[PDB]
Structures are given as C-alpha cells and as structure tokens.
Amino acid sequence: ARKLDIDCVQAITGFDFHGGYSHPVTDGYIVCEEFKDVLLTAWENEQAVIERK
Amino acid sequence: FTSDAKDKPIGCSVAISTYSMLGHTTKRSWEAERVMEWLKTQEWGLMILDEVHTIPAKMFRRVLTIVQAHCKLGLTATLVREDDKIVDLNFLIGPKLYEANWMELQNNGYIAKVQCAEVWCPMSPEFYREYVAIKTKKRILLYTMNPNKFRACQFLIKFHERRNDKIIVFADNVFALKEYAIRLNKPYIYGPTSQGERMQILQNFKHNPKINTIFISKVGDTSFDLPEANVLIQISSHGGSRRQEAQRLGRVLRAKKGMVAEEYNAFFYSLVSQDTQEMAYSTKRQRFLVDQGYSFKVITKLAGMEEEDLAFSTKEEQQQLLQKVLAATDLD
DNA sequence: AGGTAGTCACAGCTGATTGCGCTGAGGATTAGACGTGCGATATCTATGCCA
DNA sequence: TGGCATAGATATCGCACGTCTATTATCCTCAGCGCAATCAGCTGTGACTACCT
C-alpha cells in the first residue's frame, strides 16, 4: 500500500496482556474496497518477486 | 545519550554520550534530534573527551564544531597516532598538560610492575615455505596460526593455570582467535559478541574459578572494560599499532595486592613467529614501551614443554591444521 | 659542428583498498474486584423467682 | 396473681483468605555509516634527441 500510496490502517481487533502490559492485537489491514482489487494483485506480484528474491 | 538507554536531556546536569551518537551524520531518531537541539541551545562550561587519539578522525572532529563548549579536557593513556595527526590536535583541544612517569608509579606501587616477555616461536618449515609462497595479505594467517606457537601457548596456559592466574589471550584475527579457543575449549569474544553473553562470560571470569582463560578479539581495547588480570598473552597483531596494543596492555594489567613487594606482579607475553614480518611489527610496536622504560626479554626455549603433552604433537596434526588454514583462502 | 629545449623512462606522495567496528529500522514476545469462610456480636422467648 | 432478671436458641454483620483478568510496550537482528596498514597512478627527476646558429 505504501508503494501504491493507498491508505492502509491496521485493524485493531483485540488486546493482549502478555509481558505484564496490555498490548494491541492487530488483524491485517483495512483498505478501501475501491483500491482493494488493485492492491491485491500487486501484493501477490510483490510476493512473486520476494520469494524469487 | 545512548541509542538503547535513553533519558530526556531536560534537567541533565551532567551528560555522558558517545562519538557515534553525536557524529551520526545519517538521519537519527526524532528524540535524538530534540537532544541535539537541547545540546546546541545548552552552553557547556566543561566537556570531557576520552581516548583523544581517536579525535583526529574527521567525523569525531566534526563533533567539536557541533558542540559549543567552553572548557574541553581530554584524557587518554597514549598519544602516538600512527597517522601523526597530533600537531593539529594541539589546536583541537590544547597542549598536553601532564603525563606521569610509568616507572615512577611502579616504584610508588600505584601500578603493577609489568613483567614483559617476547617469546620467539620458530615457524614450521612447511608453514614457512608457504609463508614465503604467499606475498599478499593472506600471508597473515600463515604466521598467525603457527602450530609451534599453538603448543607454546598451550604450555603457557597450563603453567599459569597451575599458577592460578587470570589468562587473557589477545588475538586480532577473528578466525585465529575462534580456532584457538575452540581447540583449547575456552570462551571466545569476536565481532558481534552479543552483549548479554559477553557480560555473562566476563562475570564468570571474574568470580568462577573454573573460568580463568578468556579469548578477546580487537574489541577488548576500548569497546568494554577488561576485568583485572595478571597474565596477558598477545598472539595476533594489528600490523604495528604501537599505540593500540600498548593501550590494551595497560588496560589489561592493574595493581594487584599480595604481589606488591615483588618487582614482577603482572605478566605479559608476546608470541612472535620467528623470521616473519611479525618480528618487524613487534619491534615497531614495542618502540613506545621502550620509550616508556619497559624492557622486553627475548625467550626462545621454553623449559617444561617436552615433559608436557600438548596439541599437534604429531606432524600430520600440524599438516591437518595447515589444511584447515589454507582452506581459509584470501576471501576469508 | 655546438647548446639547450621538447620529450620519454624510473623514484616518492598520496588516495583507493582490505581487514575490522557503531546506528536506525525490521520481526518476536499481578492487584482490585469477586467470590467465600470464619470470628466477634445482638436478640426474641419460655420460664423460674419475689412481693 | 403480676412484672422483669436471666438462661436458651439463632443468626448476623465485619474481617480475612483464595482466585482471576484486564480492553495500545519491550527485545534480538540486518544493511548502512565509520576506522587502521599496502599499492598503484600522479608528480618529480634524469637522460635521449630534433632544431637553431
């Protein structure tokens, strides 16, 4: 998303107390649906490079 | 002002920092930006600099321009920069205020009277033939891995352990240090040296009687404090760093109670490969210490080695070590 | 024919090079409230005693 | 016979003990910046040779 300059916010879904303090629990990133399909295909292609890398 | 332990500059009457933190030309943390701004705003009546011989470097010199300070005092153990960048240092800080007489402090008992030796280990002819064969920087591994030197080191370690002394083995080469430590089954300190493991090994060395032999690479000069010892054996040289190795020697050995009356309460030995370029490096290095009145006795024959059984007793063992070293080609 | 300037073949000076080191940005990782049992604390009632 | 001191049955509230879950920070590791001794190209030096008088 940073490469594509699209808004990307981590989805905070819970909170964990591990380590003696409550810590955020994130579940992926919530991105606007309009760019979603554009964001997905690049990401896979991104992975398609990284694995080869 | 450390990258790991951070404290707010506000209310910091006295600050302790490092050259790299202030000299970090690349982008730093946003908090570091605030610290630098506070420092520039702050007027420093006094500044203290350690290991002044390091200042002549351009990045550390820029720190002086960065910091606005009235009084700047530099403290160090040596001043013989091999790059002769000390004349300009007279204007970076000022003239040398004082330098104590080392022999005088020895007589006064403030410092341990060091007993210094240069131990000549003949090169194995097969090693020596290969030593002549190589003309490049790879030649260092040839004379730094002398099997006869290894046996002499093992004998000295046994002697001092039977004498119950703290043994510090200094070896600039990482591979040589690791090989020696693994073969002798002793702790080793090298490039990364994770800080927790480093501190654990140091504290074991200080207190645990089972651990009295520590291998320390080049990091032992100034990167951390050396626990006080009595036996310092130098195997590998930087190549003539007459100031660095002398500084590390002085840092290693300190005054010890109990042996105050004796003129030799601290023991230092330099293992030098005979007929090698290591001889010239050792002579150039000990120039400063001789200028300091310290003498070095040359010893070739080590009594008691023949009676004791040591590593590489058979020829093929040394041949196997030669195989291992030659496997480490110029890339390593 | 004779002399000195233009020009090409070997030594020092010094920046590039090969060995080692700090940073900033990554993935990894138990006491107030609630429930419960015990200890110190009042209380209604049937009946015997005295005038 | 009548009113009230006193022994019996019954809980009762305050105090302490055993147990749990909270609703947003810290700790290893890598790529990118540095320091210290050789070695080659720039520069300086000596000698060969065309050109002028």
Image (cartoon, coloured by chain):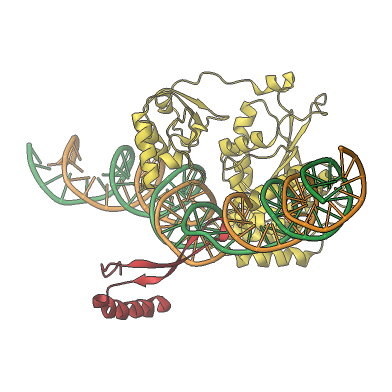
Chain colours: A red, B yellow, C orange, D green
Horizontal and vertical percent position of residue B161: 83, 46
At x 63% / y 39%, what residue is drawn? Answer: B225
Q: Nearer the viewer, residue D30 or B94?
A: D30
The quarter of the picture where the C terminus of chain B appears is bottom right
Q: Nearer the viewer, residue C26 or A9?
A: A9
Q: Is residue B327 visible?
A: yes
Splitting the image into 4 quarters, where does residue B268 fall? Answer: top right
Splitting the image into 4 quarters, where does residue B165 fall? Answer: top right
Horizontal and vertical percent position of residue B279: 64, 44
Horizontal and vertical percent position of residue D18: 73, 59
Q: Nearer the viewer, residue B16 or B331?
A: B16
Horizontal and vertical percent position of residue A23: 49, 60
At x 63% / y 35%, what residue is drawn? Answer: B286
In the picture, measured across the screen, residue B295 lies left or right of residue D28, that is right
Q: Is residue B275 visible?
A: no
Q: Is residue B181 above or below residue B15?
A: below
Splitting the image into 4 quarters, where does residue B176 fall? Answer: bottom right
In the picture, measured across the screen, residue B306 lies left or right of residue B83, that is right
At x 27% / y 77%, what residue is drawn? Answer: A33
Q: Is residue D18 above or below residue B31?
A: below
